[PDB]
Image (tube, rainbow over all chains, first blue to last red; front, side, top):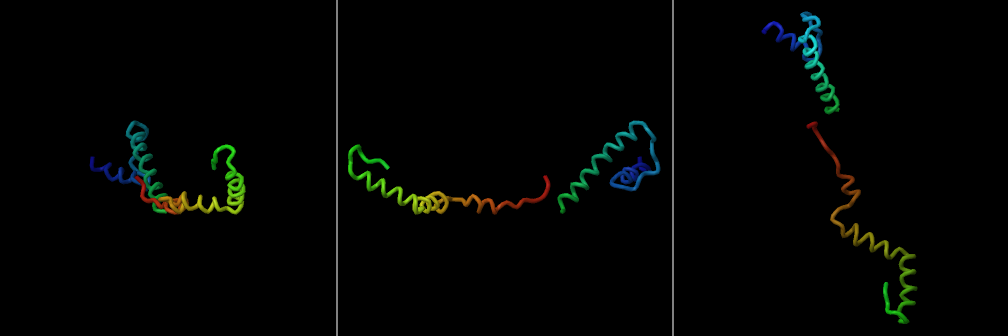
Length: 49
Length: 55
């Protein structure tokens, strides 16, 4: 629970993770939060400009 | 502009209005009582639109 907390920070913007729970729901929904947070930084770049 | 029927006043008024409309005397007063007496300038308020941060 403390090991993969960094890999959520490793899924925070960038830096592709080394530990990958290959294809189950943790892989997909771990990409869903990952999909969500990349909108926020593109919007951050769009708003600051 | 309305005068009663058969009144001789209307024809000099008919020469009056067609003169004042030709000189833009109406248009200057239309600028007055709509825009200069208006509480906004529609392009002055159009020159005031500057917004900010994302909700």
